[PDB]
Amino acid sequence: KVFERCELARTLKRLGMDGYRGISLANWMCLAKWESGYNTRATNYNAGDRSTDYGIFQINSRYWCNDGKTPGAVNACHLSCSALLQDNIADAVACAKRVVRDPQGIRAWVAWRNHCQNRDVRQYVQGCGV
C-alpha cells in the first residue's frame, strides 16, 4: 500500500520510532520517502550482487531478511523478506530498529546520506500533528 505522508508519520510515532537510537521521526520519514516513495510493495533486485531490497525501507536480503535466493544471507532480523511486503509495517519497523542498532545507525542507507543528512528535513513531518 502507498501511505500518505502524515498517515505514515503517525503510524511510525505509534510504533516507537521517534527518537529511536537518537533518530528523529523526520529522518525516518526522509528515508522511507527516498527509499520507496512510502510504498510497502517496493522491491529492487541488485543484479551485481544477487540481493533484493524489500518494502517501505528497502531492507536488504543479504543481511537482514531471508528470501532463500541471496548468497551469504545472515538474516539478522530473523524475518522472511515477504514479511516486509505487507500493508502492515510492524515487522518492517522492528527490522529497521535492528538495522540501526549497529554502529552505522541510519547511515547504513546510502539514500539517507544522499538525500537527508545535513539537510533541513522538517518538511517531512510538518502539519501531521506528530
Image (cartoon, rainbow, N blue to C red):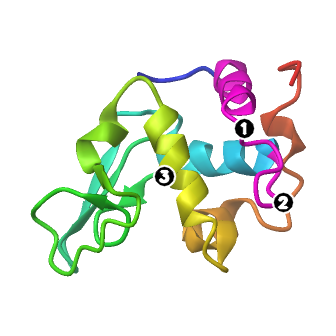
Three-letter residue code for mark 3: Cys
- Image coordinates of residue 19 in percent, x first then y, are 83, 49
Q: Is residue 15 left or right of residue 40?
A: right
Magenta extent: 5-24
Residue in front for this viewpoint, 45 or 72: 72
- Image coordinates of residue 10 in percent, x first then y, are 73, 23
Q: Residue furthest front?
A: 78
Question: Where's the N terminus, which quadrant?
Answer: top left
Nearer the N terminus, badge 1 or badge 3? 1
- Image coordinates of residue 109 in percent, x first then y, are 56, 67
Q: Which residue is mark 2?
A: 22
- Looking at the image, is 43 positioned above or below residue 116? above
Q: Which residue is mark 1?
A: 16
- Looking at the image, is 33 positioned above or below residue 107? above
Q: Is residue 31 left or right of residue 118?
A: left
Q: Residue at x 48, y 32 (%)?
A: 89
Provide the secondary structure element on which disc 1 rests. Answer: loop
Q: Which residue is mark 3?
A: 95
Q: Is residue 22 magenta?
A: yes
